[PDB]
Amino acid sequence: FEARRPKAKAVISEIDGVVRIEETEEKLSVFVESEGFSKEYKLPKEARLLVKDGDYVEAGQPLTRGAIDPHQLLEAKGPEAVERYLVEEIQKVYRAQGVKLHDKH
Image (tube, rainbow, N blue to C red):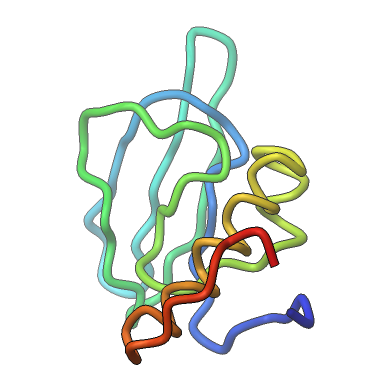
């Protein structure tokens, strides 16, 4: 409800394109690119990656595993996405606990 930076953040994809990953020792890196451009993403050691070398990632899609920051998803996929994310991500907790409250609220 209070838009905040979860500790375990998940770097979303500002760009909607295709995936590419790298090997070097210290830090991993996922690159999203379209015929237009590509964007480099720094995914440190702990970041377990959900995406694989090969397919498409819509804007604001999870590229790291876990929590997302509403502001970023706002920027990336739009209000329509933050909004829709907030609701469903909230009901996630209640549903898991038995409470059945209508999304409306």
